[PDB]
Image (cartoon, coloured by chain):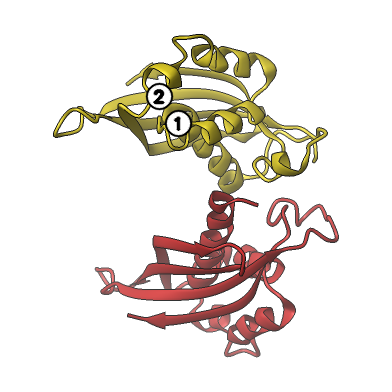
Chain colours: A red, B yellow
Amino acid sequence: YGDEIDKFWLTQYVIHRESYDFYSVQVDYTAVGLMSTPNVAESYQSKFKGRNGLDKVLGDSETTRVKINSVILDKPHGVATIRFTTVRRVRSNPVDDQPQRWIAIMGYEYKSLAMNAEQRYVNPLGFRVTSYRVNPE
Amino acid sequence: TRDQTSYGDEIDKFWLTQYVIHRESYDFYSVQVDYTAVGLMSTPNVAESYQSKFKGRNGLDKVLGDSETTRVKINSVILDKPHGVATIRFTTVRRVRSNPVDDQPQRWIAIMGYEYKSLAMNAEQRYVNPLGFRVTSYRVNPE
C-alpha cells in the first residue's frame, strides 16, 4: 500500500500493543486483535487471562507510554523493524521510571475482509501482523 | 471506497499531515510522487490551484530543479472531525544547494477542509490514496 501507509499501521500497532492505559486498553485490545492473525493475537491476549489479567491486576495504578524512534521496511517480504522506547509511570510515585529501549521485529500483510462498522474506524485497509517479536538493545 | 467525513483522530491526522508534507515540501527526487499524491488527495478546485505553479516553462520543478530543497516539520494538529476541518502548524527548512547552511526555519498554519469519497480508482491510485482521502479547502498563512 506504500511505505508511509505501511509505517503508520505498524507504528500504531506497536503503540496500541506496547502501551498501557486502563481507560483505553479496551480499544487497544480490540485494535491489536483486528490487526493480528488469531494465533499472534491470542499470544498477546495471554496477558489478559483469568483475574491475574494485566488490566485487572495493574488497574489504573500505573501507565506506560511508547515513543517511536525509527521504522525500517522490507516491502516484498512484508517484514519491518521498529525501534521504540517505553516509559513506565506509577501514579503514586513522583517521577517517571527510567526509559527502556526496545526493538520490534514484525511481519505484516493486507487482507480487507468482513467490512464492519466498528472495524472501519480501526483497520480499514485490513492490516494484520503475521509475526510479532520484541527484544531489548 | 466509502463516503465519510472522518476516520477518527489518528487516521485523519495521518492523511492530513501526509498531505501537508507532500504539498509543502520540495524535493526534486520526489516531486513527481508528491505532485501525483496531492492531485489524488484533492478536489479538482484544490488541485488546479496547486498544479498551477507547475505549469509552463517556469513550472516550479523546471525552474528550481535540484538547486534546492525544503523539508517539513509538523508541530501540531487540531482536528474538528464533525466538520472535516483541521488546523496544522508546521515548520519549513529551506536549503539552497549553493549554501553551506540551511535557511532559517519558517512557521506556518494550514487551515484545511477534508473528507473521504468513494470513487473509481485504478491500481496505482488506490496504492497512494486507498481510502479516497481528499482536501476540500486549503489555505496557508505565516505564524
Q: Secondary structure at mark 2?
A: strand
Q: Quadrant of residue A95?
A: bottom left
Q: Disc 2 versus disc 1: distance between alpha carbons?
A: 6 Å
Q: Position of residue B67 (x, y in %)?
A: 30, 26
Which of pointers 2 and 1 lies earlier in the amino acid sequence?
Answer: 1
**Which kind of residue does numbered mark 2 sit on?**
Ile
Query: Which residue has dot 2 on it?
Result: B109
Q: Secondary structure at mark 1?
A: strand
Structural crowding at the residue carrying mark 2, measured as other residues with C-alpha within 10 Å and reported as few (<14), some (14–19) or many (≥20): some
Residue farthest along the left direction in this orientation? B100
Tag on residue B80? Answer: none
* For residue A98, above or below residue B40: below
**One can see residue B61 in this view:** yes
Q: Is residue A39 left or right of residue A72?
A: right
Q: Quadrant of residue A76?
A: bottom right
* For residue A118, above or below residue A81: above
Q: Position of residue B3 (x, y in %)?
A: 79, 34
The residue positioned 54% from the left and 82% from the top of the image is: A54
Q: Quadrant of residue A111?
A: bottom right
**One can see residue A90 in this view:** no
Q: Position of residue A88 (x, y in %)?
A: 36, 73
Marks 1 and 2: in contact by CB < 8 Å? yes
Query: Which residue has dot 1 on it?
Result: B88
Seen from the viewer's position, the closer of residues A3 and A20 is A3
| Chain of the residue where label 1 is placed in the rendered structure | B
| Chain of the residue where label 2 is placed in the rendered structure | B
How many numbered badges does the structure rendering display?
2
Seen from the viewer's position, the closer of residues A81 and B36 is B36
Residue farthest along the right direction in this orientation? A114
The residue positioned 54% from the left and 17% from the top of the image is: B50
**Which kind of residue does numbered mark 1 sit on?**
Ile
